[PDB]
Image (cartoon, rainbow, N blue to C red; front, side, top):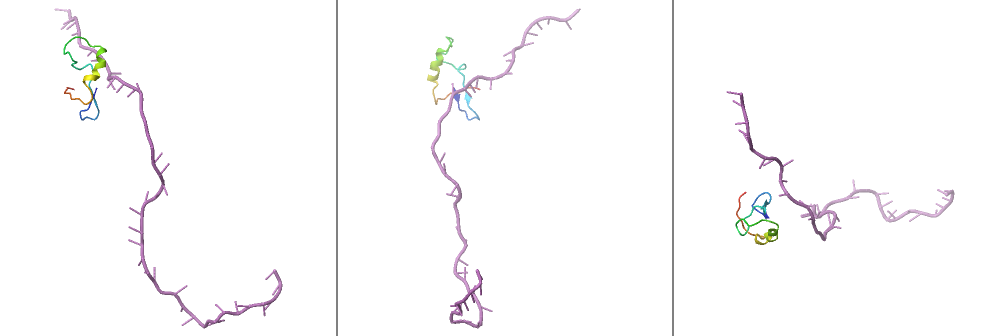
Length: 50
RNA sequence: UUUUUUUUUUUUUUUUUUUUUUUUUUCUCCUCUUUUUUUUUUUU
């Protein structure tokens, strides 16, 4: 994703670092990549750490 | 007669655009004197 945080550039939120739905150890593969662009859609608000 | 362990050079690229020299001011302004105006003519 690309996040705007009033900086000189854009900030990148990698898919590898995200608490995906389920919130536990089940699996992480390319099947999630199709629905990753579904829940964190355009114009949402997050609160993360650099 | 002095062993064992302490990772490293950001990820990304396959974006659209249908105009045209210049460009924008300055006011009214007393002309002195022999004249009517000479004139054909010929040699270029």
